[PDB]
Length: 47
Length: 46
Ligand SMILES: [Zn+2]
Ligand SMILES: [Zn+2]
Image (cartoon, rainbow over all chains, first blue to last red; front, side, top):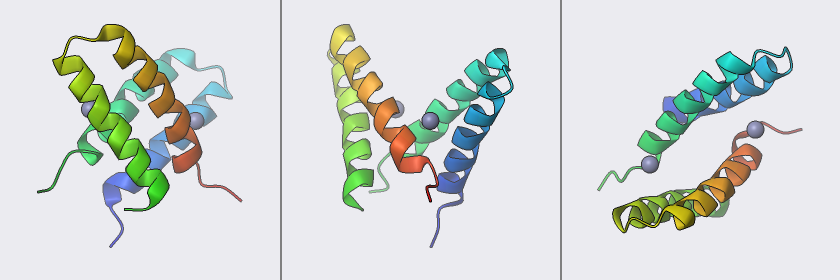
């Protein structure tokens, strides 16, 4: 089954590029933190 | 479990190993590689 967390990562990564494309660099830097946090949890071990 | 996903997972593991060993320059380099590879992997491409 698809991870909703993986989709959340894809979405925030896309959002970061979209925000950058509008010059919203302060929002970008906060979203980068969120992206890194979501990846940190996604790449933890289940077992 | 795909090869490019596993690669990112493993870099992430190595980041935490390097942090636990206080290797700041190693961490910085690994983070750079992780972010580059993340970009390519998680972008939804044509
Ligand atoms: Zn982490
Ligand atoms: Zn990117």
